[PDB]
Every structure is written in structure tokens, then in C-alpha cells.
Image (cartoon, rainbow over all chains, first blue to last red; front, side):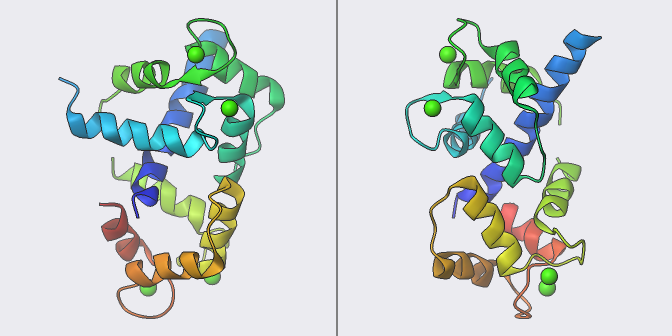
Length: 26
Length: 142
Ligand SMILES: [Ca+2]
Ligand SMILES: [Ca+2]
Ligand SMILES: [Ca+2]
Ligand SMILES: [Ca+2]
């Protein structure tokens, strides 16, 4: 029941991780 | 300034990754989630992702490290819900099926039964067509 809203923030955490790498690569 | 609700929000997200409950997110658990979410991360960029936030160089993300990077960027959440729907609706048909919802929870390693999945849709499906549309999906998240 508390699974689905967590998926929303899980997605954001991946965008942030990928942004942190791209920030470094540039 | 970090509310008790944001922290629990971040804790629930962490526990989705940490499938084994050892308190750490590994490349395996990170890659497993990203694939369930429709992405295909290269094993090297998985390593580079852990590397950005691993402060003590053990090759894992723990909760405070996870908390640290989520707390830095709390600038505003609707497109977040929208994109999330786009992830679940694989055939782009505008409805999340039980199978479209099964194939994500199965890929996540949620270890849920096909009836457990079908009860998740049942709670969310308001108009009774057997599928979850975006507006039903919104109420489920919010
Ligand atoms: Ca682990
Ligand atoms: Ca660590
Ligand atoms: Ca469908
Ligand atoms: Ca519907």
C-alpha cells in the first residue's frame, strides 16, 4: 500500500544520481 | 527543516532499493530498479552513480548518504507523477493493466502474488474498467 508513492521518489533519486554524474562529466 | 514526513518518504524509497535489508544500496539493487523502471543502465554508469554519493568509498549507498543527496535538491512534483505513469503504461495506451503493473513489481523483486497485484489495481481502479488511468493513478499516489 505504501509501495506506489515511494516509486515516485525512487524515480527522482535516479534523475538526481544521473545528474550528479553528468555534472562531473561536464 | 527536514520534516518527519520527508524523511519517512526518503526511507520508504531507500527500502525499495535495499531489497535484502542490509542497509546498503549496491549496483545490483540500483540496476534492478532502473530496469524495472524501463531503463537499461550500463554496468559502468551504475558504478559511476554509486561513486558520486559514496562518501566512504565502500561501493555502496547507505541511508544517510541517500538522505544527503535527496535533501540537497528538494526544489519542488506533478510531472514526477506523470512520468511515473508513463513508466507503468508500457504500451502507451493510457491505462496501466494488471500485467503492466505485474511486470514492474515482478522486475522490482517485490515478491508479490498475482492476486496481491490484482488487489492493488482493484483499490486504485475507481471507474471499474479493470485498468488504472492517469487520474486514478494520481489519487493512488497522492
Ligand atoms: Ca546489498
Ligand atoms: Ca556507505
Ligand atoms: Ca493495456
Ligand atoms: Ca480507467
